[PDB]
Image (cartoon, coloured by chain):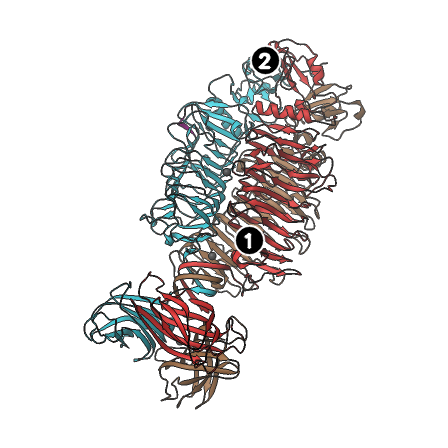
Chain colours: A red, B brown, C cyan
Amino acid sequence: LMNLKGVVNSKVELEGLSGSDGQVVLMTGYYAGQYMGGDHFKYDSTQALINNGVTVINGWVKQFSAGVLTVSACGADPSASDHSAALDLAVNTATSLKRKLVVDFDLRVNTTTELDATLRIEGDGGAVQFSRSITATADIPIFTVKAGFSSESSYFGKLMFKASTGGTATAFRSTSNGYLSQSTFDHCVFDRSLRYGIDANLILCDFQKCDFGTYMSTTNSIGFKAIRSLGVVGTREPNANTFYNCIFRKGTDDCMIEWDSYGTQWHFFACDLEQNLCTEALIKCTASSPIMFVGGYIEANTSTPYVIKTLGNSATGFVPLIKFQGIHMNRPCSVAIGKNTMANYPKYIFEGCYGQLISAVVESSTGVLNDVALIENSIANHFTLATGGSIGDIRTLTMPSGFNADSRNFQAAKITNLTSYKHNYKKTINRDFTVGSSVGVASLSHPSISGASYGGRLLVNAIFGTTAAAGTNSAVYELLVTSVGTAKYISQIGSAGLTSGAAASHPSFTWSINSSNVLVATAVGSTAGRFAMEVFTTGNVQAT
Amino acid sequence: MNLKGVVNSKVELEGLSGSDGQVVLMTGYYAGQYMGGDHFKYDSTQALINNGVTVINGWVKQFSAGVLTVSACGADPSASDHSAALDLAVNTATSLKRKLVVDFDLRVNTTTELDATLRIEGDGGAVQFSRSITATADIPIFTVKAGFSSESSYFGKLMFKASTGGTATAFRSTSNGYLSQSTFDHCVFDRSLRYGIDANLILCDFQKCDFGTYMSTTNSIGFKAIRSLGVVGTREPNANTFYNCIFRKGTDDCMIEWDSYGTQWHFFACDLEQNLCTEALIKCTASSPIMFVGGYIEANTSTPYVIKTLGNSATGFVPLIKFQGIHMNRPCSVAIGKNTMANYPKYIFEGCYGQLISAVVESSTGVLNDVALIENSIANHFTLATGGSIGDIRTLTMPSGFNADSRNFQAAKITNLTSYKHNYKKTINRDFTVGSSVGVASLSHPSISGASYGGRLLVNAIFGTTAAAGTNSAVYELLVTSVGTAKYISQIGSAGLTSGAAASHPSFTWSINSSNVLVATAVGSTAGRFAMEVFTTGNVQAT
Amino acid sequence: LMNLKGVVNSKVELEGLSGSDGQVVLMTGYYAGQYMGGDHFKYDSTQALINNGVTVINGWVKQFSAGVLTVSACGADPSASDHSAALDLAVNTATSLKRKLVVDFDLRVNTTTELDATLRIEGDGGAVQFSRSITATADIPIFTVKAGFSSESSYFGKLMFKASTGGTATAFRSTSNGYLSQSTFDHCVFDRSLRYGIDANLILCDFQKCDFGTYMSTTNSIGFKAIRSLGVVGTREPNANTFYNCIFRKGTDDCMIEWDSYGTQWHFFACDLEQNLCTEALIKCTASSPIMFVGGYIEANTSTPYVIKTLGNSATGFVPLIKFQGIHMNRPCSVAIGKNTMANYPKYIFEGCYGQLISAVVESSTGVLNDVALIENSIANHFTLATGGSIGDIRTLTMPSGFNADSRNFQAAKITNLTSYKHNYKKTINRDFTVGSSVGVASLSHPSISGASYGGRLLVNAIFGTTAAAGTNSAVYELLVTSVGTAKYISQIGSAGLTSGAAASHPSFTWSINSSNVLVATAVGSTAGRFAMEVFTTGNVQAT
Ligand SMILES: [Cl-]
Ligand SMILES: [Cl-]
Ligand code: NA
Ligand code: NA
């Protein structure tokens, strides 16, 4: 038969207590007056001199009656002002033992804790702002990501990160651009008292309903940025970071989210980016690969110029597409939603977005607002224009006259009602003539078969000057053209306007085709000066 | 020291006397039970304190398991009710800022107000054998407080049932109170409930939840998954996302419902099948787009519509309802999308696959398959059963249909284009007498306002209004251009009845007046009602 | 006040221990020398003869001091080489008691354990590769899915599956293609030592941050396949399986993911498919319904021919669309991303993809690379071509001359600059003429109203032979046509080229309209031989 040896109230009373093999004792709390970290202990004479402070304490082996490793069982004193060394022993023990770590009371740390690989740490606190919290009492990262991949694989479940002094510290920081790789942030809250929510090189990390800056334990006057992932081009780039139902509120730095090194695949599913006060943009990134917003909100950012601003050199890499798929955007920014610093890229898709604008939709690298050349598609969008808002030629539900996209190429199309006046159209300007001189207008060729015999119709509108206006001398010519080898065939079907050259400014010309298949215009009568032609082709001929 | 002893109930602990530091083991909160048990240390400073959970006449709960359980708050498994125990549990867990765990199935006849920051979880089985909470009265299991007082919560793996089918609900709002910033992780909603959730949801995500698959007791009145009623302007149901959720066997007027122009309700890979709703699957007075990104909408043969939008478009509206890659095997009986407002919402069907016993959309005026409501229709496959119809909407098996109503591009290269009404204008009711002149269209430069225009016009004039078999017809080819007040028109050619041999012949000579109007003058005996159709080319447009 | 009776060190010491009603004992571990499976026990004389091995042991009732059911409390011996019978009792106990099961130490099994319905089993191990593991010491499935729906409803949280011998065993297998239905795989890791990660018929299963084949405990030379779900057509189909942020690396079988029976709705949100060595494709499936990739990576698979290859008979079912929405694709395969076995289907959408190609974009069932007829849409894509890469006529950001899609039909459209030369175009070949003979070219009719009076202009380009080339005899004709009942009206507005028939090879013709509304050409002069016509219509007339 075996009886209970006794009960102890602290770890100091356990190490000084002597026993024999098989004896079991009850410890009520790691420290006196506490109930946390307590556990049953069985004595082992083989390890009587072993005392690591957690599992074995001078022969007393932890029995894990609760089946869970807690930070209190590693020396975390709730009455103490600091728990840094206790947390370090907790991460080292939980990872070396290959078991999850549980934070059972709010910790306060003044020294960083390096993130050991495969760390799974969870909190048993309340919901959202009353979750199990870890506060940084100094201007130091709560966790330090190791260099290279030494911190790869981790799990952070329902933990809150605060700072004792507003505008200091961060939850994570990387040494030598170390990778915070293959991690999960489940319902983690990042208090606005932090200077940076996450200042580590993130890769392959998913965020499940995290919160950045909604709640604020102490006032932050320096600034708050949600994420800053800085890496190295080619070897350590911030990649594959997805956000589900996350919230980004009350930012005060130059941007809320930032990453460089042409990091790839940052996407936001049903996220909420509102009530920020960023000075430049909500997302400032030197990135490649597309960036997509699948549902969510981008609103209430009246003082932020841009929603997203891409940087870098397009020769090295670029974002091809930024898609806003069904985003509620009630005043998302103040200047333009998408700001480009490279030419042409990125393109934008606004699919079913809804809200009111005090800004432009996009801005090119040269400052052109609402550049349709940057609009890959714009369908089913509803935008009301407030003071400062503009859409330009971009199509909306209330502005059907705009364009859905810049260009589309199809191999076939059936359009019932088509409106296109510059169809097979070519413009040639600065056609300077003297009396009776000849000037080439365009080159004729078969549009499908190279070097083949062409044949079609030409509508030429010649005017005096460069661009037509009210009272501009005009003339129209209808020409049938075709070729058989060196033989050129042109027939003027008709004409109208000032076609006789009664004055120098009259666009009067006779048409021919030379040996180079060039449509040549010869001045008629007194015609002389600078003219401009516009050719509209039909059939098996093109004017280039 | 030594262990003081073992007790079998809470009443045995409070009647037990002790001194400071003494530790006792309680085996269960009530006699004959092994739940709610914990170690207790005596504290003479709190000898008169007895809240029933943490301190019991000086005995402080030691949390040997490290978790707060509803059984440790007075929940008696042998008792028929646990209402007062649950209220004390949520109040204790929230005030202590720690998670609450439901360790056995609860039965409640009085509501429990949702305290803020409540994290409550269950340790039961999977799906239908999860930790369950049954309402033994027609009352909400949880009551959301008014305003934002219930904001922040977490519900993990909890099933909600009703002792009587067709009664009670898991959640209800006081004065349209906000159920804000919550998460429903693998929560099951039994069909015995009258409503799965009858609260004003906002900023809530649903992770693999189930609505109405399982049924504990027969419900003859009806089951609705979600009904969120709010207040316009101040409390609107917004930002509610559903991932991999299941909605089966609904029997009310709809399965999902929200009003007040609530925004951003999206469904990722959800399953809406086997329902028996009388009106629609989703009946909502909503604004902002609504999206279905993957999933199923099928087996709803008795449900008229899949989604039906309501409200006034002047206040707000849904701009787009996108069905992105949805498997739709008989999703409804009349039309997938039913509109109450004109024009809005537009619809996108991207890669959908299934069989139709209904139309695709129905406008506010009842027009089935109104292509004006189709923002895009690409890569869809729909098999037509009895009652199914697609109209002019394009499918993989019906390429003759249209992908969309309209698209505007600044540039385009189309290899093979089919467009006969290109730069086309029709003018009817052109009544002529012998030699009279009637304007047909206004000419202008199509890109530069007021500039000199110049191009060609193809005019097809007919007798009457609309062409038919044997209709007198005539075609004219005209070159036009202008220089200030000077108008230049040249008839390149003509064909047909162009001489006016009879009154019904569409014979006209063409001119341009000072108002830049293309004027037709009757030729010969031409008199009566005629109609023209103009096709322009070049720097001229007929308006 | 009753005192604690004593302390026990094993389950065998409890069953041999006698007691009276109400007495409580403490067991330190289920087996001697162990601290797991321990719990408090209270004696019940009514159940003195009951001994199920977990809850009641010869009258001693388990008190659940920790409040959690563990596999160690069901007979799992850490010192034993096998835990199969203990695991089987654990699933039977946890499901019959309707409470979650916890694996507190790594298990090793040589016999399968059938999946009881509603099983919720979790692990308390580390993160990712150091998670709580279950190893199969034989060529057997770790879990066996029951036939039909008998295993429906389950939850697997943070568990890892390994094999003692590389290339053997699997985590799941189905009896009679039984349904692994309504399950969740949360952060589960599948070691590459397995022959198959999952070889069961999956349906209504979601995968949350799972890993397939990144880590390899022991060397696998036979092969590793991530998922293979084989079902029955009509009755047992693998449906409704969604993957969020999952990783698929280093496959060595014929494919990485496989399912048949025209299973529906397999989607991949922000998944990672890279560094595989698959022999045929990454995804080989006989599937129906669309397949979508919303963000993620498909790269570094230089030895894999295809990314996805659909099979089956389109009469039974087919995939209508395979969408790659914003996918990073740096060398995703070696021949073609999409391989079709059926005609026409599936269609492909590449929306904002970014990467480098050593392959084609698609390959049809007849082997045609980059068949534009299979491209439903291709917008904002950036693809750099390496050796073996090709896009054909598919449009990219750097190759704007390509097509975004094969065809689009709109009821209305406003295009500022339209380039379309085969507009309202018809070609008729093999027009064989003798001296003065007549041959029909096309049928004329109203394009909107059936049988109504048509009226418009026709541009006809007649050539000698069939297809135009350099030096081909050509002639152009401009015709105004209209009809009034049996009366046909045609007027040659003009002509150009070899229109007089001076030689036999000249395309010289006179145009008329017969009673069948056919545009008839009559040879002029000496014209005789093989000719071809191309007609371009305008107005209320069409040439068919
Ligand atoms: Cl499109
Ligand atoms: Cl079993
Ligand atoms: Na990567
Ligand atoms: Na007509």
How dense is the environment of label 1, judged by Cα within 10 Å: few (below 14), some, or many (20 and up)?
many
Question: Magenta stretch: residue A182 in it?
Answer: no
C318 w.r.t. A521: above or below: above
In the rendered view, does B428 fall on the left or right side of A538?
A: right
How dense is the environment of label 2, judged by Cα within 10 Å: few (below 14), some, or many (20 and up)?
few
Residue C1: image tag: none
Q: Chain of mark 1?
A: B
Question: Magenta stretch: residue C168 in it?
Answer: yes
Residue B290: image tag: 1
- Is residue B32 in sight in this rendering? no
Q: How many marks?
A: 2
On whether ligand 1 comes within 8 Å of the CB at mark 1, the answer is no
- Could you tell me the amino acid type at mark 1? Ile
Q: Foreground residue, B56 or C509? A: C509
In this picture, which residue range is highlighted in magenta?
Answer: C165-170
- Is residue C405 in sight in this rendering? yes
Quarter the N terminus of chain C occupies: top right
Q: Chain of mark 2?
A: C
Q: Foreground residue, B11 or A268? A: A268
Q: Position of residue B402 (x, y in %)?
A: 43, 61
A458 w.r.t. A160: above or below: below
Q: Foreground residue, A357 or B355? A: A357
Q: Describe the element under mark 1 as helix, strand or loop.
A: strand
Residue in the picture at 53% in, 40% down: A240
B130 w.r.t. A449: above or below: above
Residue ID for mark 2: C18
Can you tell me which quadrant of the image ligand 4 is in? bottom left
- The mark lying in front, picked from 1 and 2, is 1
